[PDB]
Image (cartoon, coloured by chain):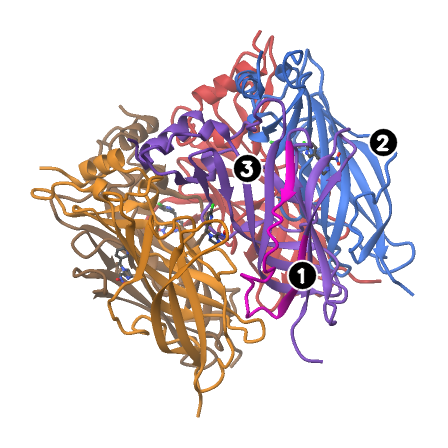
Chain colours: A blue, B purple, C orange, D red, E brown
Amino acid sequence: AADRADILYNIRQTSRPDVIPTQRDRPVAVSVSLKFINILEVNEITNEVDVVFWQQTTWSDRTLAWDSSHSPDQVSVPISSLWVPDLAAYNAISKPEVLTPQLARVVSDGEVLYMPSIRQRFSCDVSGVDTESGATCRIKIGSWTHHSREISVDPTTENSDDSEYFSQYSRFEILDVTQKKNSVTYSCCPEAYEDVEVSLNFRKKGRS
Amino acid sequence: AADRADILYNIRQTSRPDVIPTQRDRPVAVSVSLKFINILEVNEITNEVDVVFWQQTTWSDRTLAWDSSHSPDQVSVPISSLWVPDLAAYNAISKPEVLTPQLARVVSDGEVLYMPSIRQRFSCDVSGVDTESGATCRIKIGSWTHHSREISVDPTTENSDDSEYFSQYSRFEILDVTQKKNSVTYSCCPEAYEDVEVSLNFRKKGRS
Amino acid sequence: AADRADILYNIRQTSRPDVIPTQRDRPVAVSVSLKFINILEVNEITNEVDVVFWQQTTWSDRTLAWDSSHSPDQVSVPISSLWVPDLAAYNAISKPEVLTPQLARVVSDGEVLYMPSIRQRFSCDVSGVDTESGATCRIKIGSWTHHSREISVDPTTENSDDSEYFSQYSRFEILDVTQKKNSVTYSCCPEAYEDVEVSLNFRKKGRS
Amino acid sequence: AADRADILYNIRQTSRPDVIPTQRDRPVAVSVSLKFINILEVNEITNEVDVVFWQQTTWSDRTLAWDSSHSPDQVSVPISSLWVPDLAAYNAISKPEVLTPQLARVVSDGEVLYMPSIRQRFSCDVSGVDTESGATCRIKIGSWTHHSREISVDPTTENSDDSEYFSQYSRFEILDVTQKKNSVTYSCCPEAYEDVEVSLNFRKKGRS
Amino acid sequence: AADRADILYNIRQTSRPDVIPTQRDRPVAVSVSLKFINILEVNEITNEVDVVFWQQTTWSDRTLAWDSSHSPDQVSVPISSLWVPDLAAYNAISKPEVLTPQLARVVSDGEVLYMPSIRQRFSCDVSGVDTESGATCRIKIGSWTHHSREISVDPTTENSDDSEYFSQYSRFEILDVTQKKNSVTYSCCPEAYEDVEVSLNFRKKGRS
Ligand SMILES: O=[N+]([O-])/C=C1\NCCN1Cc1ccc(Cl)nc1
Ligand SMILES: O=[N+]([O-])/C=C1\NCCN1Cc1ccc(Cl)nc1
Ligand SMILES: O=[N+]([O-])/C=C1\NCCN1Cc1ccc(Cl)nc1
Ligand SMILES: O=[N+]([O-])/C=C1\NCCN1Cc1ccc(Cl)nc1
Ligand SMILES: O=[N+]([O-])/C=C1\NCCN1Cc1ccc(Cl)nc1
């Protein structure tokens, strides 16, 4: 009869925060979805935008699974005690500013969810933000050091209201957000690196 | 009997900072209460405010309980030695800047009080701030990863002077502050997350 | 004899940085005095000031005492190795920017001295800063979690020249500084908290 | 027949982060290559630029080698666990801001690859940035404390688009980039510190 | 013979980062020399300047000495493994932004050198910066907690051009640098603290 103190204790034993949990010989499947919450400073001259969003991130780590028959099925764990994808926004020009406690949710079957609220500035296409069609800023997120055979990233395919959580007090409004996937092979290495491109179509409110 | 050294030593032995102190199978009852100290910046156009407040937070942790029979009934302890509610302001657009020493007060009975002074920026309704009826900025604070069955949040209905500790030198003045309990559900999970909605009715000071 | 290394080793053995060193069952007498070095960014419209000052702090911790008959009677020690009063400036709107090496000076009898040069911004009365009588900004500094029975704060009775170390290059000049003691009771607790009130009377320099 | 866990373990076990991994008695051969991603802010009056670039850095540490016949021959490793070249931009006027996860890639032969995306400000010739011939900002990168006998610096001679990864939304465009091997010496001593001079020839984009 | 790893281990096993390396009861003789690299933000209205310099620091700890007849004569060591002078710029109004890897150089005879490149804002006489005679900004640096009998600082009146490494791209030029020494007693203690005062004579570069 283990409690929550036991679950965390035995997770610290099996978990290796620096060892990607590749099962057999397959890549770790990381799903990523960006819940846009706000759009702050926007500079059409420099093509920069300050965005706030909840980066819903999920994956499975079997080395964490336990028996939930006489124990809770889920627990909150500091991410510093788990392995986490080394995701990076390729066109970000400031490091990600995490606004929420850095805790992930771990399910007895090894499923992991981490959804930090992040504030980050980006280099993207802002032109057209003050027009009916709006501007389309594309955000590219993917593993920085794990190629396609170690980590694959796919947008959590779930038809959701693009502005379900978007602040109603923002000067901007979201016209549409589309998430796509891509595989790129750089110089350094022969293997491909997967990324997800989130396109944020938005414009200023109250235009003539 | 014992001294402050023993109390902290003991807290050190039984305290589990990363384990939510749920006694039995019910949620930890956390009380939240904001005391507004200042309103530094307000933007009528972007609907943004920069404020300073004391986030009075209390909860119970049985494991820390000790007999004050012949020793102090209270000690100041670094929050890094205790478990703390993973509270977050859902509409905040900046990381919380804790202006005070990160020490919590622990009562011999396991009661915990943590009151950090915090400066933080929020996205909220600033319209009407320049009028007699002022503006109403609602700030939502609740656990980030613990749903209703693990954490409950309720305000401290201590009907006091909303501007009791408010700075007299601020450019704004407080008209009224009300704290309402609120529940919310999201995608990830079926169970809802509780939060305390703080309505700050304030306006600019002056004639006209 | 004994060397500075021995002194530091033993200090580290007896020092309980997280335990207030109360003698008998009395409060630790903490002396606080400010030496103003500069006045940087004044704003009479927002009633905010950016100030640089030396926070001369002294207290006693007998549990760090040693025999200096054949050894040195003083050593510099990192503050992390010592218990330090959890002092806070009640009307500060930015956390303190400690500009100096965080080392405290310890005497063999247990007297501790810690004097960091601090740059911090405050919310205070800036009205009249550009008039002959200048403005009077009052700074309140005291323990954040230790009430009167645990910590007592008193302004060092000394009387250095108010602007003896104040930069001659500031746009402003000090007209007078008075540091008075004070006590305050809150909503959380029946026992009061002590604080020193420092009144900085200053003005922008004239011309001719 | 060892998995990634054993590999990383071994690496954390034999790696000496503070000891230069000198093979026999020849300097450590470090290769440095900059891949400009953006030119954020430019000032022709103060000869100062703000640029983002991927700093491709490679070297060898034979002690980390492991038999990958029946095991992975490449793992991601926290640079904190490894010895890393103490490279510095000699004409940088700001601390390098690493925007990406600080992980290096280690091959089973001891080859170490580290490519952090960095944002940093430099003091360099910006004159002509607004002409068809644009400006030429030269950035010097080399070891800060290891002269030529301890560390050698060489540009990863690899033909490729000078702006293959440069932002298309930037306000500037890259005309050419030449990375030349070179060295620096100081009065005091005969010691010679090798570096890589990266010539960034760019100009303001024409709105046409 | 001994390799670099053996040299480090010996250093780590005898150097005491928190213990000043005093000889008998003689004060540690520290050498300070500033090599200006740039003069960035300059404000004659507020008398503030942003300066980038190499803070060449020298001292010795003979207990770290080894035989280099058949072993390296020098090694780079993280300053966190060494005792380092607690130097502070008295008229600095910003904490130092260390731009270079924080590694020192220890020589086999016990000498230790540390040359961090630093950017710091100073409060000093900026008046006359736009004239032929320019301005004279005096920078004062010395130990913060070690008086004259524990540490003595001396300006290396070595032969070297003032703007030998000074940037050509700065909006200013150096006219003459002179280093003097001083000793001061403060309202806290009886013993005096030494310091080196650097007078930087610079002016706005003009086509005259
Ligand atoms: O949108 N969601 O699915 C969920 C949430 N949005 C804001 C807080 N929230 C709850 C939550 C659940 C799991 C984790 Cl790891 N972090 C936060
Ligand atoms: O408002 N209050 O109830 C109490 C306080 N306000 C400012 C300092 N203060 C004292 C205090 C007590 C306990 C804790 Cl945990 N922190 C601060
Ligand atoms: O540009 N490149 O050559 C390579 C890359 N650019 C972005 C991610 N990427 C992959 C990568 C591989 C190993 C390391 Cl150490 N860092 C990054
Ligand atoms: O001026 N010098 O003699 C030497 C140097 N100036 C800038 C870097 N540099 C090399 C150097 C030497 C010793 C140390 Cl400890 N750090 C850097
Ligand atoms: O003003 N004073 O009394 C003393 C000082 N002012 C600047 C440096 N200084 C010396 C000093 C002594 C002890 C400690 Cl703990 N810190 C600084």
Q: Position of residue A52 (x, y in %)?
A: 71, 47
Q: Is residue E95 left or right of residue A192?
A: left
Give the amino acid at mark 1: Asp
Packing grade of label 2 (10 A; few <14, some 14-19, many >=20) is few
| Residue E6, quarter of the rendered image | top left
Spatial separation of the CA atoms under disc 2 and disc 1: 41 Å
Q: Is residue B150 magenta?
A: no
Looking at the rendered structure, the secondary structure element under dot 1 is strand
Q: Quadrant of residue A32?
A: top right
Could one spot residue D25 in this view of the protein?
yes
Image mark 1: chain: B
Q: Position of residue D96 (x, y in %)?
A: 54, 48
Q: Which residue is mark 1?
A: B176
Say if labels 1 and 3 share a chain. Answer: yes
Residues shaded magenta: B151-178
Name which residue lies at 58% across and 68% down: B170
Of callouts 1 and 3, the N-terminal one = 3
User: What subunit carries mark 2?
Assistant: A
Of helix, strand and loop, which one carries label 2? Answer: loop
Question: What residue is shown with label 2?
Answer: A158
C-alpha span from label 1 to label 3: 26 Å
Residue B176 inside the magenta-drawn segment: yes
The reply, left or right, for residue E77 in relation to residue B23 is left
